[PDB]
């Protein structure tokens, strides 16, 4: 009576559902695993820590494999609420991973902001904000210990952990470049803030120490890891003024099979600004009041979702001079692509086109082999920058082919490509199997 | 071995409604205590402590702290 | 790794009308129940010891037939040009001789009749002992089954199985280690002319004409083969090699091609082999088998 | 042009990606399952329902397995919007799981809040709150039905569903303790609310009805299930307002393979409060205006994200007299560990340290088995509660080691351990494989 | 066009291939057993270092007219035998391997487009029906020859083989399925062996043995539905099986695939009888 009344109602149309059952949902079996323990210790930083300086962190061989790495910065505010925007990862300007004397990849200030913008997309990006930025309207003088997790190929999943028990003759180092200008801590815009103290930096590395039986195998057998790289060269935008619509052809100097291309349009002096400024709430400093300035962002709200303030009208990607797909408007790459491949929201001004079915995961699922493409380009068409940013009625009520006049400040073009390589581990040395 | 009111005899049916059993559980109910007395004395140091058998040589100072050997050493 | 607990493989194989059909007339089925990791089977004082080290180790009637090895099936999937023991896909990880590093999928049994479903492994691991490279994963994609069916009459039918998408090589049906204490080696010819007792050479290879085999030191084990595949569907001149080797303690072989055919491909289906074994004094074995 | 461009541009590195294919993404083969139906069936409750009263349910065999038990309440407000904070969880004070007469598990009001704080943090925390709290600024007298899904080992995934047909000779029952005080329903702060009606409650059990061939196997075959348990005893702290950065070393009493430890510093009067009260928005009643009272929270906003209002400066776990990892500051366990281990937001004041790669999951991934060690101690260093809770300039503007003078109210130390055990079911009777 | 008015006449026999493709001339020989396919028509020679005819060979044919034993009107044939030279027969594939040819042959109407006697039924010289042949020569001297017919929604009479033997076959002998002894009866020189006949042999001195292997039958319930086979043993040798010898309107034939397997082999009359007696 009830569940039974449905249970017995078995026929022909559910034979292909429950005939000759192979699985059940009501008795799961858990696969036993090699024992291990998670240990997290402090690495030594060689060099002077400070703004604009460079230090080298030497990873010790205290455990057998390396998994998660988190870099701490202790600093204070130089301003009121809303004057900062992820200063922790602006400070962590560049991180370069070197294994045995050769480089793997290099992660840039805005890459960290981009990955967070277009892959870490659920409430975890609030958690991330809490780790890297000021969230609770903190005031001048407040002190906070920031955590900037690194997002290298092995920093999210244990399956690609660095087998340092194998790599006994070739060390792994982390090279850190720190920003000389951090918004709201040392400079407000370009205006230096007096009394800005230097940060305290610490690099924490999570070691896996595992059972002697598999530990011994790790130390002796060769390995091949599905190591992933990030490749990057910065470029320049061709943003128009008014009555004229610009376009430009960027040559994509990428190699090795990719998962996606991700690009943003940046104001060089306002970290994280991918959109134009407008006199609307959250778009510029003082927005909505008589003191509103559309040349200075509301730093804490720098990232917005109003693509009307986007500069990009349309784009298409070419391979060997042939179009990959027909022209799409900028809103396609901002809203449709992250939806079809990842399932989150990408802030305005940041764009992605995927090749992989699951670019968020690490199981290969479709790649563009740029090593076999002799001429790859990205063709960008811009919005006409004719809207008067100072008039709320002008930015909130205009058409799709135009943008704010303040968009002309987005002079830096940053195009990233995420690609595959093979990390080969053999008799104490590790390195990258392909280089193109 | 049973009083009559207990049940109708099961025969000539096979719905598989009821279980067969011994009607008593003990150690497998409560659960096996893995600690024993092994944590009264201690191995705070990490190397495994070689065992000297608890031979109860003296009649007055026997003790009951168990061998306490680590199941698998670090090596 | 290459020594990972297990792996998966995909093989693409297509053909049209260039494949003969070898009728695997023998097959296997089960009605038994899942057991754990050991069998002890007895009937008529004939015991079978099936340890966790691998499922067939010893047997006898207050005696043993070896100290070290029981029966195993295997393959020589590719023997490019008659080369050495490069790819033996044994059911026993005899390279270790202590851990059974062989994945077992199902172990059904009932009293008197155990079965088996297991994968095989590459006997040589990854070490290229020849001039060619061997394989990748230690555990291969071929599965085997067994049924050891004891019949009230005091006889047991031993079924083994092999399968692979394609092979044009040499199969190993049973690798057996019968003790050296079997002085008399004797077999009957299918022409029923006589029992061909011969021990002067101690080099016995019983070819197609050999009907049934027996060995004893006056206490005997009988061997009577029943079913093996053949291209008996249309009887082409396609190769179907069936023979025994008794130059070693004992081995049963089956071969499809002399390392390579002219231009012929392979069914890729299931292969089967049903052999009847039975035990008793020299008299009982001879008296029973002489019934046929 | 189009897709054929990349397919012909095939290379050598691709042997690691698309050479000798093993799988495809465009031909999914589905596994056929065993026929079943799910039904929500009301079970009876023994005991007088009311505040401070205890009740129990002896769960009948309506079906084959139990997949999900949800407790529900009918409650009325004793106050206006903002006077409540997860009152359904405060009311469901103790839930005890008994299978055959012996305790298998027991969960607490505060644990439900802790689990929700840690693990259930996406859109599900909002829908969870919709089930357990008042979310639409409801006024005095509003009535709604509340649902409190239980989270024992058989409620989180159908693969751990409790087979009753496998346990015919043991009773399966739940005990419920109903809190004598529920904030915003019976008491406003510490004062009784006149006209507070007693609650109405029902315990719904969702049964699995599965077909005969598998049902027979369930009854006839023995089973072993890998199950979760919650270990818990509460303690107290001594957070100073002045003269010392106090330390505390609390001896832990845990056994069995532990997946993680989690803890908070609660207010024994204000349910779910893990941070200090302050005259800043959402931090106390009337915050931001002259009527602000810093001794009473703005209950609907009890949970916050400002670690400045926490009392924990640092912690480490010491095993057998030796530190298993080096000291971390308190914000580490509130933000970094759940980032690595869970992937969501943890509200301030709730802390976790994992032993596992994926403690949010069901399958074992690293444990600390406390049954083999001699001394498990959690070492805490506290913040000095020496800034003015009523002055935003101080609450939003100070250093890492100091917190609000009101923070000392967080005197309840709640340390939880989540562990594995094995449930053994044989011949219609069950129990635990191991028990200490 | 029919629904469920046909019995299960189960064609247990079927033919398949494991051979390769070749062009337009085939000669197969092994252990003195040879077949000659000159592409004038599929089979012109057979035997073991002997021949049986010069101009006629093995073929399969149909008798589509069931008007109570009428004359040769609706005879679909495998060979353009009347011309006896111009092989105006479309062949689908000509396969071979060692000792084993295979062929798929599209049949033709024997009489052509003209009527004969009184009536006819013909839409063109070439017909849609495909016959199959397989000749597997076994190294022991036994050769298995299979034939095939497939005619949808039929009620007909099929001729399994037609072959012409040499006049040098004076001794006729057949074995009755009682296996009591071989029946040496040659006084008629025309033997019609029905169900009771098991195997036959013919010889002037060295013999050709015949042993049937498989023929379609309704063996699901063994109904009384007409399933009759016979030999026509005269100088010319035909093997046939009737399903609808008359105009049957009450019950039809499924019209699916039907094949026949016959085991042919050669050797001394003694060896032929001994080979069968042993089985």
Image (tube, coloured by chain):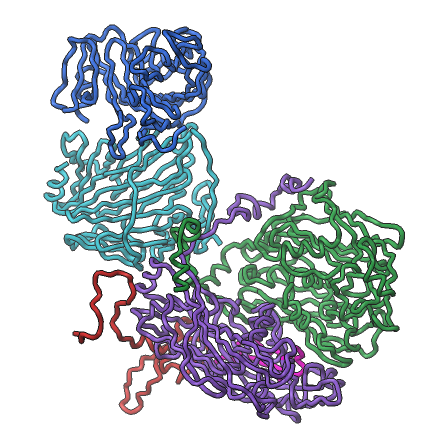
Chain colours: A green, B red, C cyan, D purple, E blue
- The residue closer to the viewer here, A103 or A8, is A8
Magenta region includes residue A215: no
Start and end of the magenta stretch? D303-330
- Quadrant location of residue E69? top left
User: Vertical placement of E196 versus A300: above or below?
Assistant: above
- The residue closer to the viewer here, A378 or C209, is A378
Magenta region includes residue D323: yes
- The residue closer to the viewer here, A403 or C33, is A403
User: Vertical placement of E236 versus A5: above or below?
Assistant: above
User: Vertical placement of C190 versus A293: above or below?
Assistant: above
- Going by the image, does D336 lie left or right of A19? right
Residue D371 visible in the picture: no
Residue D168 visible in the picture: yes
- Going by the image, does A280 lie left or right of A353? right
- Going by the image, does A322 lie left or right of D179? right
- Going by the image, does C218 lie left or right of D145? left
- The residue closer to the viewer here, D94 or E227, is E227
Residue A310 image point, x, y percent: 78, 58
Q: Residue at x 14, y 16 (%)?
A: E183
User: Vertical placement of D88 versus A213: above or below?
Assistant: below
Q: Farthest front residue?
A: E250
Count numbered badges in the picture: 0
Residue D143 image point, x, y percent: 57, 79
Residue E53 image point, x, y percent: 31, 8
């Amino acid at each position: 009576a009830g569940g039974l009344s449905q249970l017995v109602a078995y026929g022909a149309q559910d034979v292909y559902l429950t005939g000759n059952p192979q699985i059940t949902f009501f008795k799961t079996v858990y696969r036993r695993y090699t024992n291990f323990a998670i240990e997290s210790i402090q690495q030594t930083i060689n060099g002077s820590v400070g703004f604009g300086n460079k230090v080298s962190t030497q990873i010790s061989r205290n455990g057998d494999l390396i998994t998660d790495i988190v870099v701490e910065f202790v600093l204070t505010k130089g301003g009121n609420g809303g004057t900062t925007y992820y200063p922790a990862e602006e400070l962590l300007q560049d991180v370069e991973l070197e294994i045995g004397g050769q480089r793997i990849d290099k992660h840039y200030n805005d890459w960290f902001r981009t990955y967070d913008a277009l892959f870490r997309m659920n409430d975890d990006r609030y958690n991330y904000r809490r780790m890297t930025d000021w969230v609770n309207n903190e005031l001048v003088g407040a002190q906070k210990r920031f955590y900037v997790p690194l997002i290298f190929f092995f920093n999210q999943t244990p399956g690609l952990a660095l087998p340092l028990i194998a790599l006994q003759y070739h060390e792994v180092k982390l090279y850190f470049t720190l920003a000389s200008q951090v918004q709201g801590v040392n400079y407000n815009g370009s205006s230096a803030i007096a009394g800005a103290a230097q940060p305290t930096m610490s690099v924490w590395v999570d070691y896996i120490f595992l059972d002697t039986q598999e530990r011994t195998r790790f130390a002796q057998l060769p390995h091949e890891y599905l190591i992933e790289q990030l490749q990057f060269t910065g470029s320049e935008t061709a943003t128009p003024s008014a009555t004229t619509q610009a376009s430009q052809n960027i040559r994509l100097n990428f190699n090795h099979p990719t998962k996606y291309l991700a690009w943003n349009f940046n104001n060089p002096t306002n970290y994280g600004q991918y959109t134009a400024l407008a006199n609307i709430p959250g778009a510029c400093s003082g927005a909505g009041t008589a003191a509103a300035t559309v040349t200075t962002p509301d730093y804490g709200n720098t990232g917005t979702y109003n693509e009307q303030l986007a500069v990009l009208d349309s784009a298409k990607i070419q391979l060997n001079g042939q179009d990959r797909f027909a022209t799409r408007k900028g809103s396609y790459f901002n809203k449709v692509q992250p939806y079809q491949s990842i399932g989150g929201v990408t802030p305005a001004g940041v764009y992605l086109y995927s090749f992989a079915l699951k670019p968020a995961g690490r199981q290969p699922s479709g790649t563009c082999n740029f090593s076999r493409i002799d001429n790859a380009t990205l063709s960008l068409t811009y919005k006409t920058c004719s809207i008067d940013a100072t008039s709320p009625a002008a930015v909130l009520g205009n058409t799709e082919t135009v943008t704010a006049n303040t968009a002309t400040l987005l002079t830096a073009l940053n195009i990233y490509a995420k690609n595959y390589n093979v990390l080969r581990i053999m008799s104490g040395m590790g390195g990258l199997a392909y280089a193109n | 071995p049973k009083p009559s009111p207990e049940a109708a005899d099961f025969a000539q049916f096979a719905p598989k409604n009821l279980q067969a059993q011994n009607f008593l559980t003990a150690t497998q109910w409560i659960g096996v205590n893995t600690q024993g007395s092994s944590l009264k004395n201690a191995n705070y140091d990490l190397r495994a402590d070689p065992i000297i058998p608890k031979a109860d040589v003296g009649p007055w100072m026997m003790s009951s702290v168990d061998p306490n050997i680590y199941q698998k050493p670090l090596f | 790794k290459f020594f990972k607990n297990g792996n998966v493989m995909y093989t693409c194989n297509t053909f049209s009308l260039n494949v003969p059909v070898n009728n695997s007339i023998a097959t296997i089925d089960f009605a038994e129940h899942v057991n754990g990791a050991v069998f002890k089977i007895e009937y008529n004082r004939v015991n079978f010891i099936a340890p966790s080290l691998y499922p067939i180790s010893g047997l006898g009637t207050a005696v043993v037939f070896d100290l070290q090895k029981g029966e195993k099936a295997s393959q020589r999937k590719i023997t490019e040009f008659g080369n050495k023991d490069i790819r033996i896909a044994d059911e026993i990880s005899d390279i270790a001789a202590d851990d059974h590093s062989v994945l077992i999928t199902t172990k059904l049994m009932s009293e008197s009749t155990p079965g088996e479903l297991s994968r095989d492994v590459v006997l040589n691991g990854e070490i290229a002992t020849g001039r060619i490279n061997m394989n990748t994963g230690f555990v291969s994609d071929i599965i085997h089954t067994k049924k050891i069916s004891i019949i009230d009459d005091g006889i047991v039918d031993y079924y083994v199985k092999i399968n692979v998408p394609a092979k044009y090589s040499h199969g190993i049906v049973e690798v057996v280690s019968g003790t050296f204490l079997n002085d008399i080696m004797i077999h009957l010819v299918r022409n029923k002319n006589k029992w061909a007792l011969m021990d002067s050479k101690m080099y016995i290879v019983n070819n197609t004409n050999g009907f049934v085999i027996a060995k004893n030191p006056d206490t005997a084990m009988g061997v009577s083969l029943l079913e093996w595949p053949r291209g008996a569907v249309v009887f082409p001149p396609y190769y179907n090699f069936k023979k025994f080797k008794n130059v070693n303690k004992w081995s049963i072989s089956q071969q499809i091609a002399s390392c390579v055919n002219t231009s012929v491909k392979i069914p890729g289906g299931e292969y089967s082999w049903k052999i009847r074994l039975f035990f008793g004094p020299i008299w009982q074995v001879q008296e029973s088998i002489n019934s046929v």
